[PDB]
Length: 99
Length: 99
Ligand SMILES: Cc1ccc(C(=O)N[C@@H](Cc2ccccc2)[C@H](O)CN(CC(C)C)S(=O)(=O)c2ccc(N)cc2)cc1Nc1nccc(-c2cccnc2)n1
Ligand SMILES: [Cl-]
Ligand SMILES: [Cl-]
Ligand SMILES: [Cl-]
Ligand SMILES: [Cl-]
Ligand code: NA
Ligand code: NA
Image 1: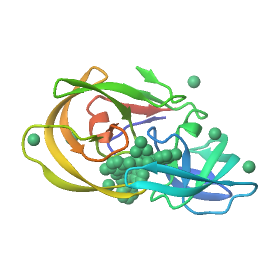
Image 2: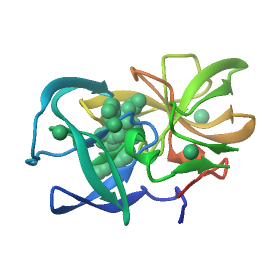
Image 3: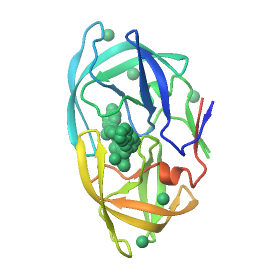
Image 4: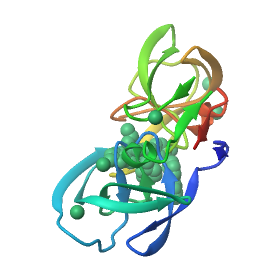
């Protein structure tokens, strides 16, 4: 698809058996999801941006279906105000910015 | 161009005759730049990021070139970690997300 930017680029994802709405975010290095359980090992991480830092749990090798496209990678879980699909998974679905 | 997302989507911008680096950020509603001098009056704005909110200065109808594409629009100035080109100006340069 071609997604214009007149509105926020929100899509449906499936993660950990759950459907969520998430922002396709070229400004985010990694994917960050609101609090949920995921299986397997994790380790703590701090991530920063406008307004400072939050503590998250880093889960590696997590499968996510993004607008119907499967990808695997790291998912950070923590108190993000918005679910964000970052570059680490945008690359895997072949997302590009075009102008 | 067609910009892939394996690296941060950094471009050169020009504002007030000065070249700066900025991130093309589909997850940002609005363009936010680090402290600089801009002409004219400003209005207050609160924006919300990953870590909470920052107060910024809103300057309207500012001339800005983005990766060689001319825009005129709103620029927010405040303590952002990186200069970010948000959707308000990504639409002016005709940017879409594609996969
Ligand atoms: C005006 C404005 C300026 C900058 C930003 C912004 O910092 N965007 C964030 C994403 C975001 C969006 C909304 C809330 C928190 C985080 C940006 O795209 C990515 N950030 C990095 C950039 C600042 C360099 S980030 O979120 O800090 C970040 C850092 C590390 C990682 N791994 C992932 C994300 C957002 C807005 N506002 C905005 N933009 C998009 C959606 C909403 C929103 C959504 C729901 C309800 N209300 C507002 N609000
Ligand atoms: Cl990854
Ligand atoms: Cl590629
Ligand atoms: Cl905001
Ligand atoms: Cl604008
Ligand atoms: Na894992
Ligand atoms: Na103005």
